Length: 315
Length: 314
Ligand SMILES: NC(=O)C1=CN([C@@H]2O[C@H](COP(=O)(O)OP(=O)(O)OC[C@H]3O[C@@H](n4cnc5c(N)ncnc54)[C@H](OP(=O)(O)O)[C@@H]3O)[C@@H](O)[C@H]2O)C=CC1
Ligand SMILES: NC(=O)C1=CN([C@@H]2O[C@H](COP(=O)(O)OP(=O)(O)OC[C@H]3O[C@@H](n4cnc5c(N)ncnc54)[C@H](OP(=O)(O)O)[C@@H]3O)[C@@H](O)[C@H]2O)C=CC1
Image (cartoon, rainbow over all chains, first blue to last red; front, side, top):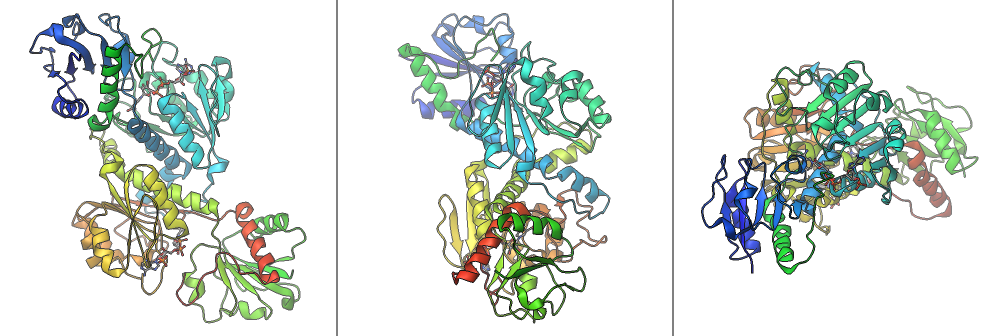
């Protein structure tokens, strides 16, 4: 006995999401809220599901019969910090296609550093052919901070390519072919062995500024630093200082403390830093829709929903 | 077992010697002198030769040679020699080398597929510009050559969700890859390849295969990767196709003349990535086992692994 789904995003095409959802669930009542103020036509009491990205303040209070919130990203740090969040299950998008895209992107980042590509790019700009003897993957230790839906998938993929892979999480995890560390006490040792490090942590009060000057100093000199998580997990000023002193040799950064990265940032002009504009992975309507309609079915049947977030923890 | 002679001006003989002796205790390994190939000891005891571009007449020093092993996966220079002895000729081709090449090809493809050169151009201008990412399933990737390296790369590309196709001389079946074969099918193979990866050996048939005409069969805006041999591509024709925008971007590990001459237009192109011929390499420790296994086989009268056809050139 399905109710209506309301959609809000200023940065996603409502019609694409609507078409995909209706293909997965014929006859689903989908209402596209208006960008900016969230105004939506129809009876708001019929709305039971909300698929959103950064909706206006008070948006959820429009819909008193809301049974389910779905964030349009894998991250929920802004959503869970809201004062108007209703006391219902909160879910995020986290499908195998998103997983694959993120894992492939992380692999690209790691391989790019592992195969000395920034050295060749620097040399190419000078018109210089200079052979550098390649290293095998087995020689290189790669650490993944976070072993969740995305982090574990990336770690497992890195392991397939022959890297000596390690992972860090909050609680114990077993992951075949990956050296698993857990807890804050183990973090220095985890970092000490990570020649290449990949940040795949959600942003929470515990992770905010985790990679500060002290944590960066635990990485071995010449480490390669990749952030595909959230910018404020890293103390950006401290990363810059560590890049400038040569403690961090190179970095690939998809996320930043302030996005877009301000024009004045020293990171722009550094030829040992690769800046991507926060697009490591995204949900695609056609492949994201099935899990959404499955959660609609579950909420109406009284079954527990997939990909539920803990609003207190923030992931 | 007889003695193995080693020749290379660009590989450390001691590392190869140590690895071979670990895999085959007591193996008589003789390091020939760089430049002229002079070696101490009785040359009649030498039965195996592990070489990279040895001097002219090098093999004629060793009349009891039973086996040649090239220190690369490619053998185009070796098989063109007038002094090559009529014995089995093998190349290095181990699963570690395979993995390294496959990972490198994956890096190249992902770099193009995820629009990285666009972000690098933008970064150099201090400009933040979002470009909506494409799923791997939307992107067709073609691999020219489906051998030890080519098939491994194609299979890896398929794991990442790309619509992968492959081209070879004779029919091949490769799970999850659209296989084309023969010269008649090449235009159609290329026409569907948004990203193309050259993984062909250099032979008279493949030399200049990717000429102006073949490049024109690729769709406009194609991304072009060469990790094979430079002369498979008509370099001047590639440059012209880059300049006209028919080829959007390229990643080139190999060139007609290596090192790439300083005057080449390719150096200064921000849509071209130049790497200095190092896509994949043999590592002594993991390459040695197959070499000592072929020594065992040649002495037992068993057929050798990774034999090349000197007439065909691979
Ligand atoms: N750049 C981009 O475009 C994108 C970025 N992201 C970001 O990636 C993040 C990761 O996604 P995903 O893997 O699915 O997240 P998950 O919620 O599935 O997993 C989070 C992981 O982080 C660990 N973790 C959380 N807090 C701590 C802590 N204080 N100390 C140690 N480990 C901690 C968890 O450990 P445990 O389970 O034991 O608690 C778990 O291993 C998202 O939250 C989002 O911020 C996601 C998609 C795209
Ligand atoms: N850049 C670098 O650092 C490196 C480059 N290489 C290069 O990679 C090349 C390929 O390696 P590898 O996969 O092991 O080689 P293989 O010898 O195992 O396979 C060769 C492939 O090329 C195909 N082929 C040959 N001639 C033609 C033709 N005329 N038309 C169509 N297809 C053709 C073959 O088809 P069929 O099977 O039907 O015969 C086969 O699939 C090597 O020759 C070497 O030059 C290798 C390692 C490192």
